[PDB]
Amino acid sequence: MLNIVLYEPEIPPNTGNIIRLCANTGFRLHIIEPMGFAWDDKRLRRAGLDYHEFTAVTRHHDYRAFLEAENPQRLFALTTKGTPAHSAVSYQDGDYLMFGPETRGLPASILDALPAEQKIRIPMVPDSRSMNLSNAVSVVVYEAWRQLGYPGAVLR
Amino acid sequence: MLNIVLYEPEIPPNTGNIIRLCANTGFRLHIIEPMGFAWDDKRLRRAGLDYHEFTAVTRHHDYRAFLEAENPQRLFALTTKGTPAHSAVSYQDGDYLMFGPETRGLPASILDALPAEQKIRIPMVPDSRSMNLSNAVSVVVYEAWRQLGYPGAVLR
Image (cartoon, rainbow over the protein chains, first blue to last red):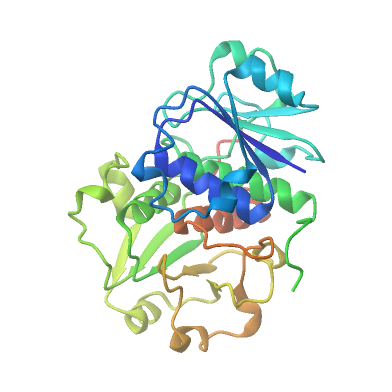
């Protein structure tokens, strides 16, 4: 059982896409408030999300409340200032995978809470530009899920 | 050198995200006309694309013209009716990776042009819903690029 964590997400369709992604992969989604948009925002549901897809989602008032509710064994953070490629890490049951907003990525007070080797990065060519957030989460999730042999996936 | 192929893409921000992705990974992008939107569409550039990112992109009048210009050694197609998981395949230099529109995915006349083991699928949990197209391309691309050891990526 793997978990995605969105810190203060900013752009409604990214979060809509990531809810779909969690539904397709069996991962749980954690959202750390405050978000830059309302759940009621029409842009969120342009995706055509079913009711069932929201039952995987947990809202946390802030980062401390998330840590108290969830008590993550291992917490990874995607950051461009990170050392190992996200595929150089060995994922395992109960890992939480954490992402910052489309603009900022994650605050120092959160990144400093993590050892260096839990701060991962998605490889890029020199002089890259920022990646769409839901693309980044997809890559990170599927590589993890692959490492685990895709438990829960239709085998046919 | 790997190549992404979008068949008649439909939704401008997906193509904008995929142009960014090609810029970040060094892949070339091929687009098979007709597209469901104009290059001039404001929705395409909400991404904040630089001029240089368009120099990786080639427009093809149709699928036959693409095959005549590019002469792909190996052509893969993502389809939900496909047998191997996209990670069960061994990618290599000069592979073309082909995707259908956000709605339809690819016409029979194109899929029939391909052997079974070049028709790949992204694993999903039972009773999945459709995946955002630029998420799907990202997963397929990064898994390929990983297999190749990320040639061209900043090693630091």
